Image (cartoon, rainbow, N blue to C red; front, side):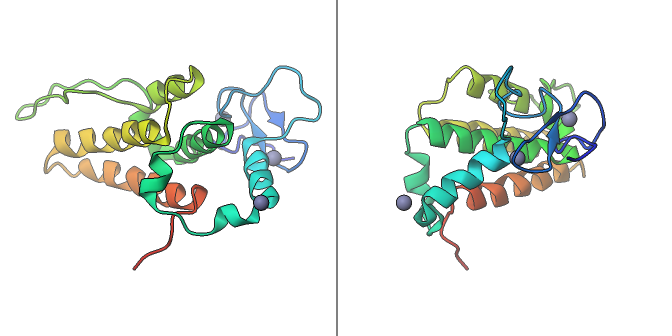
Length: 178
Ligand SMILES: [Zn+2]
Ligand SMILES: [Zn+2]
Ligand SMILES: [Zn+2]
């Protein structure tokens, strides 16, 4: 197995996947690494299994279809995996914890959002459709763009949003377009 966490790339108390060489801190993995379970497979392995079991799930989809899907266990998992892929980028640190807003010339957002809040919402099964989770995730970046205006810091928001979007189109097999 790997000697560092797949998500945050640091050593520590690691749990090891039994079906691949990745390792994880307990609360870096989403969901949190499970108490017993031997063997234990990580979320990367669980997602590969879905695809191997139904090869056709990789054929192109419309985003409008995907967003209306109810959060059954497979959609749940996929949103969990998407949230994790955003946390794998070190610039996610800017969006993890509850922000605050006191900048000359800007007002705070009406609806603050952050990664940890979405992680809790996922954990507590608060989303009934994929739409819910995708809306909260895209709001994080939209809030940021609006607040930071022409400060160059806005770019972080565009950066992490791009990672969110690429993984969204990968995980949910959105039909490729020009
Ligand atoms: Zn970690
Ligand atoms: Zn694995
Ligand atoms: Zn099938």
